[PDB]
Image: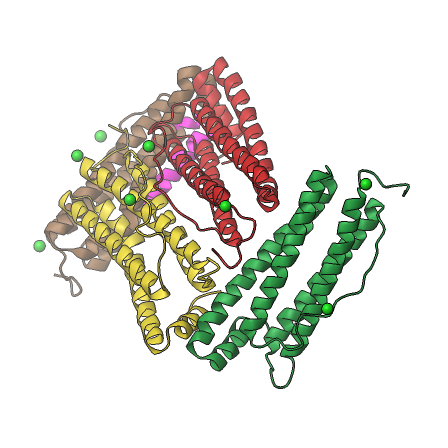
Chain colours: A green, B red, C yellow, D brown
Amino acid sequence: SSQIRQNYSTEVEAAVNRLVNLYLRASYTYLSLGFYFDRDDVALEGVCHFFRELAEEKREGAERLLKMQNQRGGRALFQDLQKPSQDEWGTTLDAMKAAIVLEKSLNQALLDLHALGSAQADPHLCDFLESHFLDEEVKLIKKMGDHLTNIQRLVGSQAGLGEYLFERLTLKH
Amino acid sequence: SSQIRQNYSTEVEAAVNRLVNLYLRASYTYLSLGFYFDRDDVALEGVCHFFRELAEEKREGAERLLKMQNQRGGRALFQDLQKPSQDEWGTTLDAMKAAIVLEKSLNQALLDLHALGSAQADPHLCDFLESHFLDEEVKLIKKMGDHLTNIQRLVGSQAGLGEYLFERLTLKH
Amino acid sequence: SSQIRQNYSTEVEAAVNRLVNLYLRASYTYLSLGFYFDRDDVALEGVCHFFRELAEEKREGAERLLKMQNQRGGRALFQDLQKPSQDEWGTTLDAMKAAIVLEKSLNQALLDLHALGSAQADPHLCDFLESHFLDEEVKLIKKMGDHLTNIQRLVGSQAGLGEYLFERLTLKH
Amino acid sequence: SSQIRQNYSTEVEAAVNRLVNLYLRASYTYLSLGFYFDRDDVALEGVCHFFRELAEEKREGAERLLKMQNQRGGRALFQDLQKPSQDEWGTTLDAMKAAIVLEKSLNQALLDLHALGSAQADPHLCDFLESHFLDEEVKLIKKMGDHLTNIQRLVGSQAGLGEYLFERLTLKH
Ligand SMILES: [Cl-]
Ligand SMILES: [Cl-]
Ligand SMILES: [Cl-]
Ligand SMILES: [Cl-]
Ligand SMILES: [Cl-]
Ligand SMILES: [Cl-]
Ligand SMILES: [Cl-]
Ligand SMILES: [Cl-]
């Protein structure tokens, strides 16, 4: 009903609101992951910083989707944000596995939205996802896969020592 | 089977390896074109530099495809590189015609890979080709068409003199 | 038959073309080694960078040989480039052993060409190899031997941990 | 008989004095070539500058040989300098052909001196020629071959016009 709305389906408008909820939920999961690694009995600063930076990136993604929703004449609708799936995240290896599962779920939601845009002949939506989300997700998932391989190679050798070395020598602090 | 691989078909993975082979073969053809124009009995420096710069551009294209293959969780496979189609490349006109035929063949391979990505609903692949290859190829083919027109206009007038003037006044040296 | 050719045997001209093929084959082997270490299930960035830099160095060596071939009035001839000897390169230790075998084979080809130049009384060729290839090869082989010793000392202690430490603390990233 | 002379044969000492005479004769030939192109009825400034720069390079070569003669404890002996082979040098094409014949004669004299040094087991002499003469000569002869090819391609088309264009667009002025 908006004065500007053109070629923007109700199906895509609703799917964009659901994707905003998924990105904010992911940002909240990363806030929990980051503060868990800042616990005095965990104390892996580089791991905390890696996840806190991802919490910011996911919030930025949600904000970009909200700006686009308004640019197209859709109406942002917010839903409750489910708490993260765990209260304690285990080792750096467990946390990095949970993060890659979370990113693959966001990536699948982006791919599903792109397919909906293609089905609705909405090229601005496809361009938007391609330009600001799809490549960023593939690059992040590759970086996480690289980190998992390095953590596994390290903790297979000597668990405690390996986790410390990965946080000191790979992660930023 | 990769931990990161998502929505990346075996058909696209294989086609990406074939495209890497085509770009490296093109880079090798440009190395041969460039050194032919550096022969003492050919001696057209600007022509040598034009083709050596294209050899670098094609190698860079292959490297970008290899980085993408790893980012998606595909596995790079290298095949023998066929030698260039000629040992001697004739005049600047003959060489520029061979170059435009080579570029149109690379462009067709990019278009075929884009169509495969569309058929496999792989938008990251389509975005990747659109962002880093399709426009660069159209711009290069246009530049080569412009060069062919200028060389033809020159060598139709006076062959030897025309080739020297094109190398001196159009090509970088 | 060239207007400039002087004291440049057909035996040396052909051996220079074969050496160009060997350097380009080595450059291709290093491209494969580098991208293997960039796989998400290998993920040793410093190792990838070490081999990608060597791919560039070998391509530069081939280009220097081609420039010399033209300076002497010889004619560059290109042959098919055989693919690298492996598709997967194992651990950093296995890869560094394959690299030193490859470099010793290039070094032997340089020594054989120098002996041919001496037999053909071609001092410009001997000076060219001495000035731009022989010392560079001895320095590279020594660096690779040093790396092999460090990797062995590390992976004999704890394989996974040792490989990570070598990539982090010796190789550039 | 010198206090410093060591491993320096009388054969090499005499051949070095003859090579100094050849380089000074070449410098004198280039002085004549340069001033011929400065005649008001020839008037090709870029050609004059190319040959005057070569007259300087050949004089510098003779000075380097004289310094080496004294460093080894040999005794410089100077002989009459024969005048250049022509008083008038024809076209730029004729002059560039005479220059390449002159350079190939200097190159052959360098190669003969290197072979004498090898026969007399005089590695300082071989290194001296390799470091300061052999590569410079090969590079100059290649440049002259490139110039001959360009002049021929130009004057085959239209003699007067081609010579002007080569002097304006290839040679420095
Ligand atoms: Cl609708
Ligand atoms: Cl919940
Ligand atoms: Cl598949
Ligand atoms: Cl072939
Ligand atoms: Cl021969
Ligand atoms: Cl093979
Ligand atoms: Cl003696
Ligand atoms: Cl005389």
Q: Nearer the viewer, residue C82 or C133?
A: C82
Report how many numbered discs are placed on residues in the image.
0
Please tell me which residue lies in front, D45 or C116. C116
Residue B6 image offset from top left, x and y in percent:
56, 52
Let me know if residue D41 appears in the view. no
State the predominant SS element of the stretch in magenta. Answer: helix
Name, please, the residue furthest toward the bottom: A40
The N terminus of chain D sits in image quarter = bottom left
Whether residue D47 is in magenta: the answer is yes
At 24% from the left edge and 34% from the top edge, which residue is drawn? D82
User: Residue D47 in the image: x percent, y percent?
Assistant: 42, 30
Give the image quarter of residue D19: top left
Q: To which quarter of the image does residue A136 belong?
A: bottom right
Q: Quadrant of ligand 8?
A: top left
Write down the quadrant of residue D135 in the picture.
Answer: top left
Direction from residue C74 to residue B125 in the image, left or right? right
Locate residue B30, reporting x and y percent: 42, 35
The residue at the point 56 percent across, 49 percent down is B7
Using residue A118 as the reference point, say whether residue B63 is left or right of it: left
Q: Give whichever of B50, B135 is nearer the camera.
A: B135
Q: Vertical placement of A5 versus B142: above or below?
A: below
Chain part drawn in magenta? D36-59
- x, y percentage for residue B95? 43, 26
- Observer-nearest residue: B21 or C1? B21
Q: Is residue D3 left or right of residue C127?
A: left
Residue A15 falls inside the magenta stretch: no
Against D42, residue C83 (above or below) is below
Evaluate whether residue C22 shows in this view: yes
